[PDB]
Length: 112
DNA sequence: AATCTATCACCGCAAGGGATAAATATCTAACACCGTGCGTGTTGACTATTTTACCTCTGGCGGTGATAATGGTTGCATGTACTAAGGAGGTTGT
Image (tube, rainbow, N blue to C red; front, side):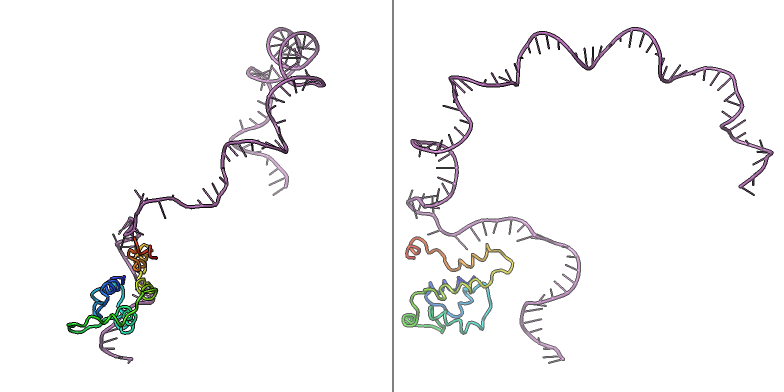
């Protein structure tokens, strides 16, 4: 399932730690795995959590990657595929696999 | 294993029925003739048997279209009766 978390995080340019339960991957339960896999969620999406800023927004601009070329932008196939429903159809798995591409049409595939 | 008297009857032996085969008379069929016409023969002119050549069919198959069209389908495996196995995880114990 996964796409909800990673897409809304990239739209926001930022993702707070606890929003892993606000936009949950409807798949898995790995709560103690988080404390290292958060690494490649942050070198291309960095954020953390505290009571309140006042003038402090800029942090992303000195601390982040720049092309989303092939990495967690596409190897995330495994982490969206990983829960195909044990007895239920190829007419389901393709819906998880297209968890990659949404609708790059009308100019994005022209840029390809 | 021979003897017979005394059964129920086959012989004892008169009658008469059908049969078949002779002679006759009828039938048909086998043939020998005749006449028809067809498949007896060569020859000849036809036209389209086959071949090859040429000019120009049919169907071999390779090739791929653009005003634009950019989140899909798919219905019923089964409702029962069993129960053996693996899977879970907290814990009260080993």
